Length: 156
Length: 285
Ligand SMILES: [Hg+2]
Ligand SMILES: [Hg+2]
Ligand SMILES: [Hg+2]
Ligand SMILES: [Hg+2]
Image (cartoon, rainbow over all chains, first blue to last red; front, top):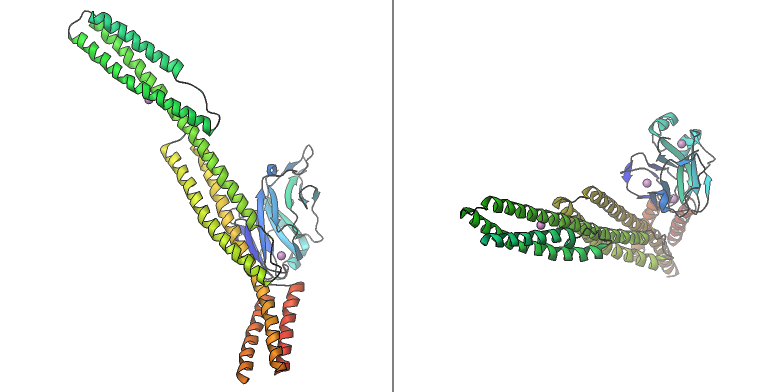
């Protein structure tokens, strides 16, 4: 995997990327999932830069920075993988939230999940960690087939 | 007689130092960069005045020493009084330096914060330019978009780097000169340097993005050109056809390389234009 600060090129061959600044942040764009050379950006924005941040109830908290992946609204032909580190953490429960255009936040859901990873990887060789190894490192795995404006990890 | 005079003069200086220390010199804290400039200018005139008074103090000391060495009955009293004028004067000198240290700091920190905020706002604007999704409606256009961006990247780079260097030097002059807020300043430096490094990369990827768009358009432009040349030969020597066949072999290779980067609909268009080109070429053979 090669490091990026906030941006990288990726095409149909795919690629596996980790932030140079933050090793745990990872983006895996499998072969034949990206239709064209495309410039991917990924920024960790502080919640108070957002004009409407995620609405939280009493015992809820953000467990990462806001994650802005771009280009905003990019569609892949098959799921891409993003791993985001989070804070140690109510209900000891982590959920992933996404906002399409920045004003409305909903919980993120994927057709695929845990078991589809092999298939998702399309024969590329990466080691993705044990779901329990991820829990020990305090890292979330997000499986998505498009980029919303923002993603975030919260605790409910 | 000389003695009476020495006392009047000592009371005078003490009263003068009192007044500078408590009423002429000020505790005000400047609101902005402009207010600091004003206060620092006023304080340096005041400090120059304190410095000059040093003459009087020395003249008094020399006079007192003359009186003691002359065996005057009050020599003990006079030397003690001078001891006090000297002390109080040195005190006033300390108050003035401290205040000057403080105003310099307040002023530098203000100056630096303006310079930094502006340079960072600048960087933000330049990111926005790098974030353009624009890929080009056609080959003539991408050629121009790519060219304009190469121009933008070099100036943005040249001008940015100089600005970052100056702020970095200014920050080091402050830290190295020893500045109550060095920790904070270093923090600012880190944030600035990271923003810069991110921007350079952002500019770089935009370049790679446009170069790709360039090839895609260059390819479709080349294919159509080739189809036209093949047509002109058909409607129509051996050397001309051979040279054409080399260009076809070359175009085929490009088509393979590109398929590697695209998938779905675009990859289909690429392959399809290759097939069309070879088909026209065969027809000619
Ligand atoms: Hg893509
Ligand atoms: Hg990132
Ligand atoms: Hg999680
Ligand atoms: Hg002084």
